[PDB]
Amino acid sequence: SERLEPRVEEKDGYWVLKEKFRQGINPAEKAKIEKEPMKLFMENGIEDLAKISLEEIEGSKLTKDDIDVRLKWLGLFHRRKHHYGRFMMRLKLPNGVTTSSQTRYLASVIRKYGKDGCADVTTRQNWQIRGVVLPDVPEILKGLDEVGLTSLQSGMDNVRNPVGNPLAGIDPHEIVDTRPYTNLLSQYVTANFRGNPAVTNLPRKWNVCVIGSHDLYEHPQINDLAYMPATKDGRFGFNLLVGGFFSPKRCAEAVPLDAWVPADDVVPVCKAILEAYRDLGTRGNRQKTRMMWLVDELGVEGFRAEVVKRMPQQKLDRESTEDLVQKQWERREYLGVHPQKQEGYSFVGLHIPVGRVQADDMDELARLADEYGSGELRLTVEQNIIIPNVKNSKIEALLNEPLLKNRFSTDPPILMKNLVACTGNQFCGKAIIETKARSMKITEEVQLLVSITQPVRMHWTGCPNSCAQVQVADIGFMGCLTRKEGKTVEGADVYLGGRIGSDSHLGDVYKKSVPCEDLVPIIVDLLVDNFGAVPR
Ligand code: SRM
Ligand code: SF4
Ligand SMILES: [Cl-]
Ligand SMILES: [Cl-]
Ligand SMILES: [K+]
């Protein structure tokens, strides 16, 4: 069979598209062919690239592709359009678990760039830092490694940050601690921080998550692979869901693979699915390359059969009938102070306004973690931060800290609690609109106008990529250009009725291309009409 012949092959320890499969391939594919991105790290190609001047780099397609494309395999994103010559940098941070000494190291990096530095918590409970310049990269990379961090394979056609339960290990109601799994996935994916070329040539990005909570903080429905906790014949394992994605062209919720694996087949099955997708995924139209297109093209039974054959021992159990997720569970709030599983300890959830932090904030967060916590922080997919492991006797002193007074509140105004916003055009070259500052301003004006009790989830995304996941929001805003009074302005498509949890739903467009200046009255009506709000 032509179709089921692997499109890529091992060639000198990297994985390259065969000469017979070059028909109709997209620009990303061409770039990957012209040079294996992983050589930048694995043959220390970065050390040489970091010395070439910026305009020497710009003079050739190969080196300009190195900086604009291949460097994303090392977690480095050139902000060509909004931050020319500087790089955002993005980690692996499985489960969102960071240390105070990681957080201090990142602060020391972004501090070098003064006002060209800052950082962000992301919608995959991850750190990004900003302001990085190419000559600093080899030392930054060494410095990440010293504090137990990697930035490998965090952008482009790679396995993205493994998402788990932000309360793993400390949650009194958790189903299973997700940390050992998200950690093993990340370790497998980066070959213990060395780089793993076997999984670095996918037809597109690939999101993985491990569910350990009844709340489904992990968003299984919108991941390429979701691991759902489930017993089979008295053994603990996971039912598998595949193909969930957001793109400008199409969104899909994850579907059952009709498969169950035992606890220690988590890595083997990740491997088998990744390998099936690598080998078989389409590499033409870039907008038909997400794994769900393969699942549709072969059918799920057809895709499933390709997973079986790449399993050790050719075996993949059928789905277990009854999973461990309580179908009727009210999602818990984690902002504020909450009892932990461990007696006499609490976790404290801090509101990070649209996930943006400065060097000083980071150093302060790291100190508060040491002084009051266990030197650990838990990042969340709503772009917030929890300090876990606070002895109850220390809470009151923590509560008085200027950081919690002036920047990161345990008790933000209702509408701010759950406000999520993607990078936007401050730095994102693909953005049509400014998100972070504007969303805060519009929400501040909105709350001044309403009494509301329900903690409405509001998501602001800068373009149709939907990195801020507007299709799961109660009200979502997707950046577009529109017309005001003849002038071309920043506007938004307004989404309604996305749901998260067990009864999840993708919302659809409520109103098209609304000028952003006209958003407040529309949002108030939407709050008043759908979410229990009472006017002025
Ligand atoms: C930082 C983050 C948004 C945020 O403010 O939190 C982000 C921002 C970027 N995303 Fe994303 N994505 C973010 C997670 C998401 C998610 C949410 C999720 O994963 O649950 C989605 C939708 C779910 C999904 O992927 O299926 C997502 C959809 C994408 C897409 C659409 C991919 C597609 O199939 O079309 C792109 C465009 C692309 O890859 O070609 C995009 C591409 C980008 C780039 C790399 C665009 C670029 O070339 O500059 C953004 C970098 C901007 C910057 O400077 O930060 N990003 N992006 C998230 C970082 C996640 C992480 O730490 O790894
Ligand atoms: S949704 Fe668009 S503007 Fe926002 S981070 Fe993603 S690519 Fe950039
Ligand atoms: Cl990318
Ligand atoms: Cl750009
Ligand atoms: K936030």
Image (cartoon, rainbow, N blue to C red):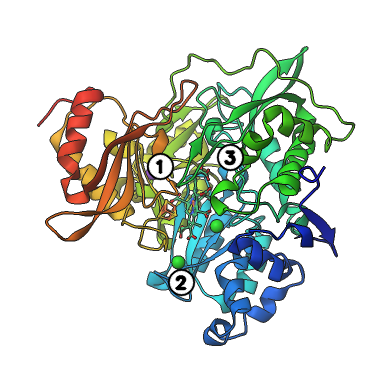
**Residue density around tag 3, few if under 14, some if 14–19, many if 20 or more, within 10 Å:** many
Q: Is mark 1 within 8 Å of ligand 5?
A: no
Give the total number of marks visible in the rendering. Answer: 3
Q: CA distance from mark 3 to mark 2?
A: 29 Å
Circle 3: residue type: Val
Q: Quadrant of the C terminus?
A: top left
Q: Position of residue 416 (x, y in %)?
A: 30, 39
Closest to the camera, between mark 1 and mark 3, is 3
Q: Is residue 461 above or below residue 244?
A: below
Q: Is residue 63 above or below residue 358?
A: below
| Discs 1, 2 touching: Cβ within 8 Å | no
Q: Which residue is mark 2?
A: 80
Q: Which residue is mark 1?
A: 398
Circle 1: residue type: Leu
**Residue density around tag 2, few if under 14, some if 14–19, many if 20 or more, within 10 Å:** some
Q: Is mark 2 within 8 Å of ligand 4?
A: yes
Q: Position of residue 471 (x, y in %)?
A: 41, 36
Q: Which residue is mark 3?
A: 163
